Image: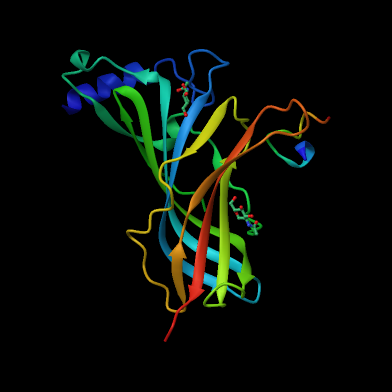
Amino acid sequence: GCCSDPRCRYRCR
Amino acid sequence: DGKYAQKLFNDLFEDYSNALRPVEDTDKVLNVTLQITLSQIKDMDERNQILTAYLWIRQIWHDAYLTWDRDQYDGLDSIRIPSDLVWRPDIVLYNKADDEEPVNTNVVLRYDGLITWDAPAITKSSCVVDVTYFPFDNQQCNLTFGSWTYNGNQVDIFNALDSGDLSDFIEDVEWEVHGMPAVKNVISYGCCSEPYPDVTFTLLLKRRSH
Ligand SMILES: *[C@@H]1O[C@H](CO)[C@@H](O)[C@H](O)[C@H]1NC(C)=O
Ligand SMILES: *[C@@H]1O[C@H](CO)[C@@H](O)[C@H](O)[C@H]1NC(C)=O
């Protein structure tokens, strides 16, 4: 998922 | 000659940040072509299902700020540069089983902004056994590469060749290399996420006959 992807991740926060 | 190589370097890096993705317009993508050379198989660990390999990673891209007019520099069209002086695309092995010394490397920067960067790497990554396909003693090892920070609208990665480069491979004692086909995967989450690309090399090993 997006939130276990370092390119995405700080964006579910 | 060397006289002008210093002048060009100074002129190029007088106002240059190696932390800024080198595109003229910020919503333009920066394309990177990646090529993996399999130097040798250091250790195929069957008990822990971990492959340790020596690779050369060749990355190619354009830097929009590192261009020059050749006739302004006694026709100099190319210079070697320590890789850490230029912005670099930040591509890493995603399926690192390894939990963890960095090495100085050199790029070749061409007058039109094209940067070629050969760099060595020692990767450790998980493998899956296959006993179904002939000769039923198989190791399938995926090497997936992608950017640590950038999405596909910022840095997009493309395979240089259909497969890894095995022209300089050192034959392993126990394992034969059946192929190393490469593919590109682009992943989008939900309806509307931006794209997330990677390139995956599938090292197919069959146990050597003896
Ligand atoms: C990136 O590559 C694609 C082809 O794969 C091309 O259509 C596009 O124009 C390129 N973009 C830049 C900024 O070079
Ligand atoms: C290895 O990578 C290939 C290419 O993307 C993929 O199709 C395959 O399912 C992967 N295998 C495993 C076990 O992850």
**If the image is split into quadrants, where does the C terminus of chain B sit?**
bottom left
In this rendering, position of residue B134 left or right of residue B108: right
In the image, residue B119 sits, relative to residue B44, either above or below, namely: above
At 19% across and 28% down in the image, what residue appears? B2
In this rendering, position of residue B8 left or right of residue B105: left
Q: Nearer the viewer, residue B3 or B201?
A: B201
At 18% across and 24% down in the image, what residue appears? B3
In the image, residue B148 sits, relative to residue B42, either above or below, namely: above
**If the image is split into quadrants, where does the N terminus of chain B sit?**
top left
Image coords of residue B99 (percent x, y):
66, 57
Image coords of residue B138 (percent x, y):
56, 72
Q: Nearer the viewer, residue B189 or B71?
A: B189
In this rendering, position of residue A10 left or right of residue B64: right
At 46% across and 57% down in the image, what residue appears? B180
In this rendering, position of residue B33 left or right of residue B93: left
In the image, residue B117 sits, relative to residue B57, either above or below, namely: above
Question: Seen from this angle, which residue lies furthest right?
Answer: A13
In the image, residue B91 sits, relative to residue B27, either above or below, namely: below
The part of the image, by quadrant, that contains residue A7 is top right
Judging from the image, the colouring scheme is rainbow
Image coords of residue B148 (percent x, y):
62, 38
Count of marks placed on residues: 0
Image coords of residue B25 (percent x, y):
52, 12
Question: Seen from this angle, which residue lies furthest bottom?
Answer: B210
Q: Nearer the viewer, residue B54 or A1?
A: A1
